[PDB]
Image 1 (cartoon, rainbow, N blue to C red):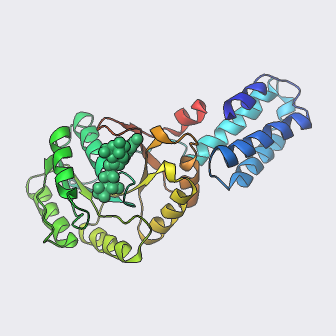
Image 2 (cartoon, rainbow, N blue to C red; image 1 turned 90 degrees about the vertical axis):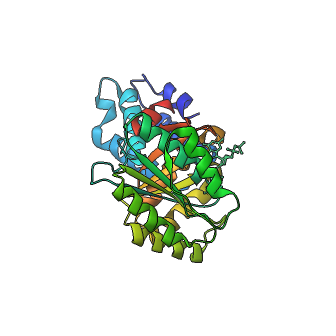
Image 3 (cartoon, helix red, strand yellow; image 1 turned 60 degrees about the vertical axis):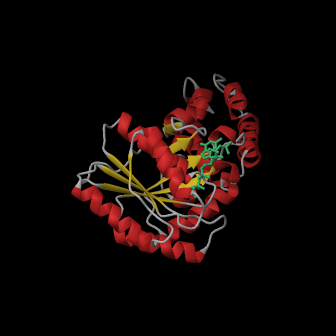
Length: 286
Ligand SMILES: Nc1nc2c(ncn2[C@@H]2O[C@H](COP(=O)(O)OP(=O)(O)OP(=O)(O)O)[C@@H](OP(=O)(O)OP(=O)(O)O)[C@H]2O)c(=O)[nH]1
């Protein structure tokens, strides 16, 4: 894939124009076909501009220089460096989970609770404002018991905004380092549901607003991301179901469309299947 052609120009000191055109065509084709990405035109142009600017042929290792340009533009396209959760402000840190139904929001709250307790030694509250989907509040409660985080009780009778305000009060009164807020989603982008997410965000003033999206959705993930970024000040993105996306380019798309970093990757169904996103790692893998 992107590996194979990039290997063929790993150590070729000639870099003839046909060799550049052939390498660029397959990277264009693999980005376009291997995944649902349509902004490849911008990536190829930047790689072409840098190659002319840095005079790759002048270098002792022109193919290595050309691949270095491709990797560096890939790392930049994916966010340059890992950005962590916004936990250096004043406790409690409020993290709002936003996204469509089926993206993986409830599972990700459990994943983040495990990650925050085991790695950052933090006290964590989880609350669910999903009074619309059936059994969802119990689903968070069960996940909280599995990951060792505390749960704030919620009921279908309550209205989402009231639930979040009450949990924030517990988080401040009991000195919780982190409050994780799970929210209801719809399966397509819905304005009414987008209006209620706005009121919940306004009430709790979240330090972190995380957009959870399914990589398997492909191009639709970027469109969903733009709509959420437009109506919410997204601080980060969580890409789920990576373990089941053979294509693998929802990542590059989202950072381009939103300008917001991917902070975490969901790589499975279990609570430990969370991995922090490192653009320089992932870029080297492919
Ligand atoms: N392969 C994979 N699937 C994921 C991942 N994250 C979430 N899922 C799927 O999402 C389901 C649970 O998360 P959801 O409750 O649906 O997420 P949301 O609906 O957006 O939040 P919400 O409940 O509305 O608050 C899981 O079902 P199950 O846990 O029953 O397992 P299985 O994969 O076999 O089905 C998974 O199907 C991931 O990282 N990798």
